Amino acid sequence: HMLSDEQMQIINSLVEAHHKTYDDSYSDFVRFRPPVRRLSMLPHLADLVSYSIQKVIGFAKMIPGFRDLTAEDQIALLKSSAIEIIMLRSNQSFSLEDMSWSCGGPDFKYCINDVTKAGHTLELLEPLVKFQVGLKKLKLHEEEHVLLMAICLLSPDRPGVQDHVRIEALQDRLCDVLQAYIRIQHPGGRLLYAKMIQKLADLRSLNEEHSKQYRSLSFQPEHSMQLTPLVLEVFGSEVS
Amino acid sequence: HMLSDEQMQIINSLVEAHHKTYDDSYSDFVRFRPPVRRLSMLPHLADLVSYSIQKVIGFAKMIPGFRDLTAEDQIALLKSSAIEIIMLRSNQSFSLEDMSWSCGGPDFKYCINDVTKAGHTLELLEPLVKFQVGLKKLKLHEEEHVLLMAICLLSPDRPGVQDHVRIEALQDRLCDVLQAYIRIQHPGGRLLYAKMIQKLADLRSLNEEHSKQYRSLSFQPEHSMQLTPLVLEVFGSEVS
Amino acid sequence: RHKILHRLLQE
Amino acid sequence: RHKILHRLLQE
Ligand SMILES: C=C1CC[C@H](O)C/C1=C/C=C1\CCC[C@@]2(C)[C@H]1CC[C@@H]2[C@@](C)(O)CC(=O)NC(C)C
Ligand SMILES: C=C1CC[C@H](O)C/C1=C/C=C1\CCC[C@@]2(C)[C@H]1CC[C@@H]2[C@@](C)(O)CC(=O)NC(C)C
Image 1 (cartoon, rainbow over the protein chains, first blue to last red):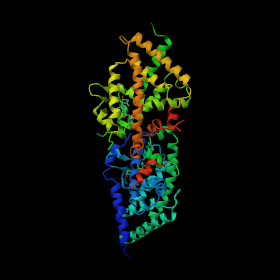
Image 2 (image 1 turned 180 degrees about the vertical axis):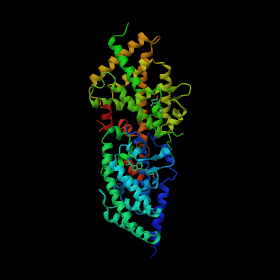
Image 3 (image 1 turned 60 degrees about the vertical axis):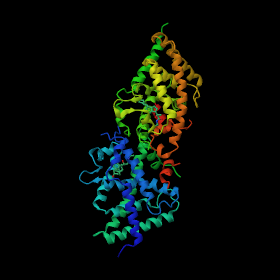
Image 4 (image 1 turned 135 degrees about the vertical axis):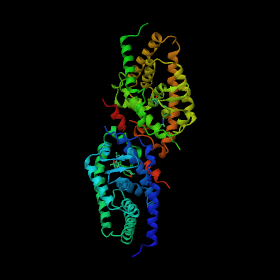
């Protein structure tokens, strides 16, 4: 088989979207509150997540059909999926040699111990690192990495979503281009689609654990005051 | 005349309170989002104001009788007076030679042009610098500088204040210790009390202009997102 | 509600 | 309301 012109255009739009929103130089990281190694890493990691939310929003706006959804559906999709998209895009800086997210220099190299200094426990950090290792070992083509982030974002099974039918038709079409892409373009990829779909289920589990950890810090005003207004909006519980 | 033991104890408590909350080394400034010289200075100056609000709160908690007020009256007093106390305590770093706030190194030296890079116009910055120059020329003893900040904070004529009678009795007693202090301890200070009281009226005018400027940036979400949660609470319009 | 989110989602 | 302010004003 061969993939069509429509499926090819979807791929081009999604990889362009990612290149426009993921900065491989990590040059804006110098603008965050500096890393410090009680909760010494929270200011820096809150600025990092806030910055990453902005990029996820930018990325989502460029996904074919996302802008056509109501502002309420776009908001419901981003509030539920943002942390899962952050965990996926972070895989690009994750290093198997160091078991850490390496964003250029040693100042922006984050290990398990650095993340516990932002208030997280091993209940989240152990499955998070296991997920990063597992994802990295899949050796995803950039086309597959960007489709997985778009599939994750366009999931209709999220709280507060109204146009379920439309969102499912968008996700289904993306899943079709991914399966076709793996089959035609990825040599030895016969079990890959099933593996990527399983990573989406691992992400639901990570999102749950993350929501518990976020509730723990957001309920302590001395810690929630270190977050940014965008993190408070997106990880918050308000309903539109 | 001579000042009493009660008035002496008030003075000691207020100067101790200031030394505990004003860091002459400016060593925490390295932890803010770095200064950058659209609205390039906003991240740094929002972190500076957020930090300064925390210090004003700490200072207020140590003013004799402030802790005895209801949480609602403490909140009403801080929301109205915070920016005026920030403008007063900032006088300690203000330099007449540079017409700028000098907080150690050149990175933490703020001139009129740096502040316009946080979204402020000359409508506020011209009277603000004129006030800083005027205050600095008064050559206030540290005892007088700390009494003026406490008098400013304990002003009963603020929106949302309930126990007006109690707050006025606290401010009156502070005004009495200031007049007595100037008369007995400040040589050639016969016109000083009247000058310091006028600075309080200049501060009401600056607070007005500041509220307009803050409304202008807080109404633009791309700019309000650069503020911290504590700045949004304290400069916000919510009523308790 | 979602003041920042609405603005970042515009155009 | 004033979640951070209440906490910073405690004790
Ligand atoms: C966000 C990106 C994308 C760009 C680069 O690849 C670097 C990167 C790393 C992400 C990491 C390493 C640090 C800790 C984080 C960012 C984790 C992903 C999730 C985790 C959390 C759990 O700490 C997020 C969080 O919720 N933080 C709190 C402190 C608000
Ligand atoms: C806050 C302190 C105390 C400790 C030191 O002495 C330094 C200092 C300086 C204060 C300044 C110099 C920068 C601009 C400010 C801090 C101004 C006081 C008011 C002004 C404003 C108008 O910009 C505040 C403001 O509202 N900022 C916006 C960006 C949120």
